[PDB]
Length: 155
Length: 38
Image 1 (tube, each protein chain N blue to C red):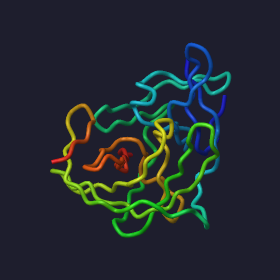
Image 2: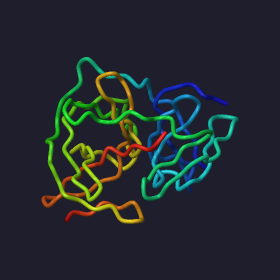
Image 3: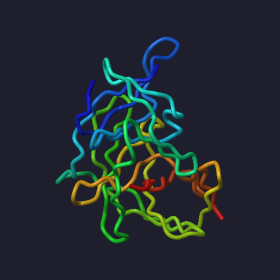
């Protein structure tokens, strides 16, 4: 029933009450979130239904109503902003300089920000307002804090 | 039954709180999408 652009909370109608499981990005008529948020289950946008279109467990990404539309990436130098939408709190931009996930296949940006597990899927933005990845898949480091990869898909 | 609700615009804020460090970590990604330190 809605295809406007912006950031969205992903909610559930569970046993008794509602609960925010994650966050998503609606852009160009496609809803982008992380797989561990929806597990490939269809979503409701008012009176209209959003059916999964593409998904990958290893990438931990899922797109609804169309292919993955987000293609921007971190430049490896400038600061980014985590558009965190925590449960019960208004959307807030958290600026930070990403670290690096040095992997077998290359470097990936990573933000050392620790937020509730209902922020999963929150977009990470560059200086031009482009989504360079989603927040929610990462590691817990040697001390106990959380570091999220900047998880981006392919277009 | 899951559903979405709009939370705001996708915009860079000209006055955002800056926090968090920039750790460089050697990790590995397995077939199940899990990161692990090396």
